[PDB]
Image: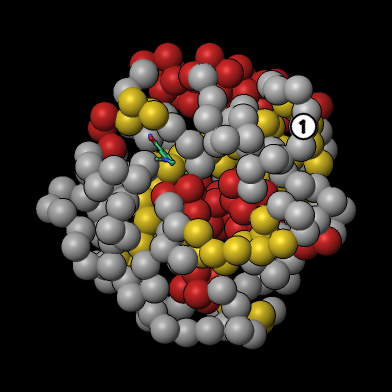
Amino acid sequence: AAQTNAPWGLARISSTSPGTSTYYYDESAGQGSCVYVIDTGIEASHPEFEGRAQMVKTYYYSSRDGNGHGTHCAGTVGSRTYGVAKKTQLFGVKVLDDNGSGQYSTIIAGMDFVASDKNNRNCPKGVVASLSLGGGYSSSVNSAAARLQSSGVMVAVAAGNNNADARNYSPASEPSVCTVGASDRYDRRSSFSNYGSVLDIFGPGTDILSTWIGGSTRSISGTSMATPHVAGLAAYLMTLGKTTAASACRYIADTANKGDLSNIPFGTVNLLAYNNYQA
Ligand SMILES: CN(C)c1cccc(C(=O)NN)c1
């Protein structure tokens, strides 16, 4: 399948060169997989989700996304126009308030929730969790992400946006999950992207167009935007049977475009997520 005039990040993950405009992908499109977006919520009513999104848990007074961040990330995972895996099932877990903030205790509870709740959902091709969030180093937060991965969920987490070593941030620094840095449309490390040995992979993160609340769209930037590209890619590859939740991060690194990014500090992987789709 081909989406003409796609957002640059979708085109990038289906190309060995920057600057293309068509997103090429297998038509299975992540059908049969499920991605939990652990964030500010998801505006499931957005036409771009086509009924494939639903809120399953909130830690606040409402399940509504009153911010937009979670809706944007969910759109990059699986919206029709802006998503990597256009036929996946999206589940929203609201651990962040409408200002985009959340306590670590709540974020941990949300991860534990997904590890259990997935045992109650039909996800025949497997389960992914996308965590476009974090703060300073916490062994408890890292352990919660490790538990979620161990339970059989492909966990993708944002590296963080401090132009610093991700070893000092969580859940970014948890080795057993998939830590995602951000790149721009010219194949440069995004100006804000964290780096370091804990990173597994880079994805498109500067100027990413996706869904927003109020049935809208907008372009924003962050490792929060790169993370759902990788989560959606994992769901897509799992539906194709090429990998599993336990092995998807390594498979994505195995098959990435290698050595093509600039301003990668020595000791950080130079790997850009790539779907390797051949029609
Ligand atoms: C919104 N910010 C700064 C953000 C976004 C995504 C991740 C993080 C983090 O600290 N990860 N360990 C921070």
Task: Answer above or below: position of 211 versus 73.
Answer: below
| Front residue of this view, candidates 89 and 67 | 67
Q: Quadrant of ligand 1?
A: top left
Q: Amino acid at mark 1?
A: Ser
> Residue 87 in the image: x percent, y percent?
76, 59
Residue 60 seen in this snapshot: yes
Instruction: Name the foreground residue: 164 vs 17.
Output: 164
Horizontal side of 230 relative to 173 (left or right) equals: right
Q: In the image, is residue 194 above or below residue 114?
A: below
| Apparent side of residue 122 relative to residue 144 in the rendered image (left or right) | right
Residue at image location 61% in from the left, 58% down from the top: 76
Who's the residue at 46% across and 24% down the image? 146
Residue marked by disc 1 = 63
Up-down relation of residue 246 to residue 12 (above or below): above
SS under mark 1: loop
Where residue 35 appears, as percent x and y from the top left, is: 67, 44
User: Can you see residue 241?
Assistant: no
Res 107 quadrant in image: top right
Quadrant the N terminus occupies:
bottom right
> At 53% from the left edge and 14% from the top edge, which residue is drawn?
105
